[PDB]
Amino acid sequence: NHTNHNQSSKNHRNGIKGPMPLHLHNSKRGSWLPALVNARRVRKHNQKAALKKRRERIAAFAAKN
Amino acid sequence: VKMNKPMENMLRAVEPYIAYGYPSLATVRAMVYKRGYLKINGQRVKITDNQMIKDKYNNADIVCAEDMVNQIYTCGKHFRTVTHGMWPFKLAPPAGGMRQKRRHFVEGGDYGNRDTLINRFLARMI
Amino acid sequence: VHSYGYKSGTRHLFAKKFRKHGAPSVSTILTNIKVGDYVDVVADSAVREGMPHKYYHGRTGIVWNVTPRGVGVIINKPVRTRTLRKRICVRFEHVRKSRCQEAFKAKEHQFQAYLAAKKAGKALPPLKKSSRMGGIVRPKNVEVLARRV
Amino acid sequence: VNYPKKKVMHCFKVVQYKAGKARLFARGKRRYDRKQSGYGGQTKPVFHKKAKTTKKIVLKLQCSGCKSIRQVVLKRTKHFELNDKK
Amino acid sequence: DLTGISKKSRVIRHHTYSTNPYIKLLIKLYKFLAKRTSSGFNKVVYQRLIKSRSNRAPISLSRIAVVMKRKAVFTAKSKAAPIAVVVGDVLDDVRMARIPAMRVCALRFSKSARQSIVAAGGECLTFDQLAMIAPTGKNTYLLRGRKSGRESVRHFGASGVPGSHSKPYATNRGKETKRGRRTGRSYKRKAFRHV
RNA sequence: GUACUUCUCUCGUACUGAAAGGGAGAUGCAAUGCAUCUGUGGUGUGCACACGUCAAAUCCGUUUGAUUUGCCCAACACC
RNA sequence: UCGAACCACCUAGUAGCUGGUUCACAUCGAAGUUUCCCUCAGGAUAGCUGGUGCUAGUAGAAGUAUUGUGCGGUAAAGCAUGAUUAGAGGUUGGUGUUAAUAUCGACCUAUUCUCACUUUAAAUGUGCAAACAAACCUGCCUUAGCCUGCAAGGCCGGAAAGAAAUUAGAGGCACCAAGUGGGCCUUCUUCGGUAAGCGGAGCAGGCGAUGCGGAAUGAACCGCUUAGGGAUAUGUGGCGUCAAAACUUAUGGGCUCAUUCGAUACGUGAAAAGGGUGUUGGUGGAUAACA
RNA sequence: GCGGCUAUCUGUUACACGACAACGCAGGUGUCCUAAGGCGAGCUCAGUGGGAACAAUCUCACGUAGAACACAAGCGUAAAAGCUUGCUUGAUUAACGAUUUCCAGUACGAAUCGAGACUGCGAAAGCAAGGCCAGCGAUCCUUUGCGAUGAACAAAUCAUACCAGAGGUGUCAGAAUAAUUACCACAGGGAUAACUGGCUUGUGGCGGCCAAGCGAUA
RNA sequence: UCGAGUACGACCAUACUUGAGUGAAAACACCAUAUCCCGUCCGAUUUGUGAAGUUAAGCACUCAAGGCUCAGUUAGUACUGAGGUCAGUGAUGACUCGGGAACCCUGAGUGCCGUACUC
Ligand SMILES: [Mg+2]
Ligand SMILES: [Mg+2]
Ligand SMILES: [Mg+2]
Ligand SMILES: [Mg+2]
Ligand SMILES: [Mg+2]
Ligand SMILES: [Mg+2]
Ligand SMILES: [Mg+2]
Ligand SMILES: [Mg+2]
Ligand SMILES: [Mg+2]
Ligand SMILES: [Mg+2]
Ligand SMILES: [Mg+2]
Ligand SMILES: [Mg+2]
Ligand SMILES: [Mg+2]
Ligand SMILES: [Mg+2]
Ligand SMILES: [Mg+2]
Ligand SMILES: [Mg+2]
């Protein structure tokens, strides 16, 4: 006995939770490789840069302090 | 409540439940003075002195009680502030009674819009 | 529950409109999509290779993926007590670049360019005027109304 | 259905896999020889109800280059011949 | 008066279910301070005491060292060494040989973590002894300590759902790696799925 | 009953493979070498920073930088 | 004691089945639905719900509107795919006729009649977006794209503010665990049936799980939803007695006589045409004479 | 209870997102194709309106699909997706990566977007990992393909293992199955019949006005 | 030399298709030919190769009808969301608070623009 009655009011008790925003689980994975294989190598460099930018900081913040 | 385009359609949709109209100046302060309560720190604190007002609104313009009225009587610039800073006016049922409650105000009952005739309806409730 | 196939109850839904059939546009082939813009997933027939399921027809959503000839679109789906960000894979012809933001794309483009004109800019050219107020209106034709039968 | 005796491959002799040797000394039959041995019922189920009449076709693309037989598997066809396009 | 506001009530843990008579002293200490002070610290350090024992995860001296080295790299280089407060308890770390002379304030220390500090050159404090030094908690670096990677939190999930790298409740580790956890057993639990 | 106990075992600090088996520090130069401490970004308590703000007076609510603890998301490395 | 005796034992056999299951108050509080099951008197799984929470949370808020922006093919409509067809008469068959004639079908026409198939054709809907990186002024790096720079990705600092309403009754996850998995009624519409207090659905509301107030009476209707009291005032329903209230209103406008008048909805429907030479109302059209 | 359908497909049901039930209606499926696959080119179908020794076909008109597309139906397509021809095996391996539908957001099945080869057809851009969307199958076992172990060592067989498929569970998320009981027994069930209480007002049987006329009514 | 001329197009009938009119330069167009690649059973189609020629078709320009597009009605009509201890009849009917058509008919007009060249 199919009814669908009380179901729309069950889905709205604890609320129909809104979707997660885009900054949640934005895993550009399973997508088109030639993009993510480039958006990978550019992440490696931008991490060598993030590590390098902190290296001068501390060393500038040492001598210049 | 304002009567913007977005707002007055929220009244259109629930008219069997509500009974609105346009408040006279004499009925706006009668609400605020006899039945006005504020949201001090999440509580329904009666408006007993003007000192209770400025501490709650703080908004450089809203000092006294006749000043909340002028913000409410006109659409105001601080209207989402003066109203939202207040509790809904828990009121008494109108003396003398209501004609009906199931039929519109124009069909002998009483709900929906009663332009400026809600004063004769709020007077019996304040 | 005899039939619940991938294309069920969809006679009028995938049917082309009246007097507009045949091949897809050259605009729809010359569109340009990025990862991130919005797209109306309006599954048209007459391509019949890459149409999404019925559900994702009036639906618009982010492009999370642009393959060579398949746009990947996330779409919010209110399943039962939560929405899934579905990840559909369709071809480009089933996709419009969604206007849904010209409402403020074109607003803040001239709204700021005049707020700047109003804040600093160069000058403040007067803009659209007031709408709802009073007025001593002068009539131009009197009338009455009783009946018409 | 028909199928060609020969397929060209760039990466060829077709045999139409029909195995079924059914060895003794298979670990699941040694068990069975032990397990259905002696008393008790027929100590195992047996497919009694009817079947899918049509049978799926494994097809062994044995390269004419010596070694490394491939296996492709076609769809369920009732009649299968290797007539090779007369 | 229809509300709908029936489930908006959050469970805040008003008090502690602990029976330790030396933490009910720290709690009355840090109700006084957390209430009759404008300290953001004392507020925060009070909810972390009344908090349970599984929620006050321990920070190893390794974690304390590294994050106090990430503070002390950007300071006046002669200003002061802030106090590493942890409302859990401090555990030694045999992966950190050399430990700085850092002051630490924990509800507890390992016997090997207290000696590792005191041998290093720092002095481990208490909270009746930190209410004497910065009771408002100026210059104090408050710390939790990892509670992920905990074996309880990585059973949380289903483990048979696509994209669920949780651990099934199974004593026999070589029991459940068969059908359902193999690509060649008619389905493999899909290691990835967008959520 | 209480008190003591080396010895051992047990769980786990390391996982993985069907198995033979194998087995996770980071950074710079390299494509292994040498100093050998969050691994990256992001969201991010508390405090210190200066930043003004009706502010009784000036301590705090505002906030912006610093480090960001836990947590989470993303994608590095490694087994 | 017999379609398998009797005693003892296995044995406290098993039972998705029936019956029962012992104190108080407080805080909250449902479900009869999803999928799977030799499944449909049961389970498992989600949902509903509680407890414990963790967490920076006027936000990643909304059963709401606005604004833009998409979507759709039901109602109504309209008859090309079809009709359905006879009414006006005139190529193709047979035929009743004296190369002259029809005759009905097919056709030929202007149509016609009223239907499912037609059309971006509603209302109601629903998808999205809407202010501190969504636009700029800039500058990185690998350059993937394309022949220095555009555009692109991962970034970024300099700078940016609003002259989409409301509530802004705090967002986010997480864990553990029940109960439920026989619903029923109802509004709106509507599939099947002669019909139903019928079966099957969609929507929302209820009842279940819930009193109170009154429709005499009733799980569901109408009000209202519920801690213990007092007062003031209402709701629905009423004011001749029962029965509180017009102590039978100074009631006002007409109507009504009914030899079973009539009189509170939904109870189920109360009465269907039909007429008159009947009592009251209205419009067409004479005479200035009715009997 | 026989009878018939549980796994599936289209329309309809179905109410302009989606969802939505009935031994609910209408139909289909458990296949068939080495081409009915792929591609390129050439062409334009059903019908009709007239024309030629023979007498169809060559003629040219007008022809929005009234045809065809392996089939059910519905969408869809006209310098094609149909027709004819050509050359072909992309109907293959796919590192399978992700997704969709069913959904519990689990399989499965079928699809969609990809990547890597190797390719075919094209001058090329592009097109193709079957014929769109129904046509299908877990654990174990058997079986073949594919190239570590048998634990005192060594060798060859033998077995097993990993890997990918096949043999299949139509009750189609997958027990290995005939009756009869009126001699029947038990647990229960008004979840469910005979019964009984109702309800259903059409059947079966009664009645009214109006009668072509019967005989306008005896 | 100026509007348009070809060829490329974007919207896709206001552009369609009809009976004609119209074509002044060019430019398309039919046109000549089997002397080659070519594949035509065919010099039809196309595909070698050019100019005796021709506006006969084609094509763009003009009017001027179905159809199409825009509107005036149609019509606040049908229909519809919501609300009645509304009225009867279990037929929808009106009301109130809103949304609001279509077919038709009377109209309006019957394409527009965008890159290069060429004049
Ligand atoms: Mg009343
Ligand atoms: Mg760990
Ligand atoms: Mg940071
Ligand atoms: Mg209709
Ligand atoms: Mg909504
Ligand atoms: Mg009630
Ligand atoms: Mg009654
Ligand atoms: Mg009283
Ligand atoms: Mg009277
Ligand atoms: Mg078919
Ligand atoms: Mg067909
Ligand atoms: Mg194709
Ligand atoms: Mg399925
Ligand atoms: Mg699959
Ligand atoms: Mg198929
Ligand atoms: Mg194809």
Image (spheres, coloured by chain):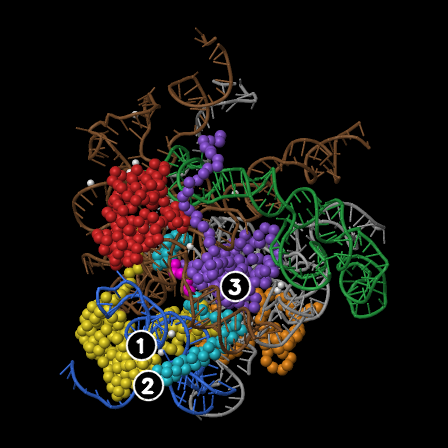
Chain colours: A cyan, B red, C purple, D orange, E yellow, F blue, G brown, I green
Gap in angstroms between the C-alphas marked 3 and 2: 71 Å
Name the quarter where the C terminus of chain E is drawn: bottom left
Q: Secondary structure at mark 2?
A: loop
Q: Which mark is residue D50?
A: 3
Which residue is the site of mark 1?
E145
Q: Amino acid at mark 2?
A: Met
Q: Amino acid at mark 3?
A: Lys
Chain bearing mark 2: E
Between residue A15 and residue B12, name the one nearer to us. B12
**Residue occupying the far front of the picture:** C123
Q: Can you see residue E52?
A: no
Asked if marks 2 and 1 fall on the same chain, the answer is yes
Which residue is the site of mark 2?
E96
Between residue C108 and residue B60, name the one nearer to us. B60
Magenta run includes residue C7:
no
Q: Measured from the top left, where is residue I46 in percent x and y?
A: 76, 62
Residue bounds of the magenta highlight: A16-21
Gap in angstroms between the C-alphas marked 3 and 1: 64 Å
